Every structure is written in structure tokens, then in C-alpha cells.
Image (tube, rainbow, N blue to C red; front, top):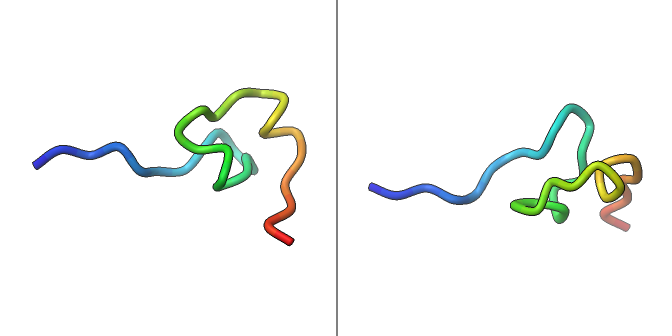
Length: 31
């Protein structure tokens, strides 16, 4: 099958996926 969902760099925000950009990673707060 195909896959797209996953975890971003170390400590990156989940919702920053699949973009996983550094800036978005630096901050993480699902609220």
C-alpha cells in the first residue's frame, strides 16, 4: 500500500506533517 502520514524531524510538531519544515518544527503545541 501507499503511505504519507508520519512523524516530522526530532521533536517536530505532528500537525507540521507532512510539511515537516524547520520553522514549524522549532515550535510544538497541539493546544
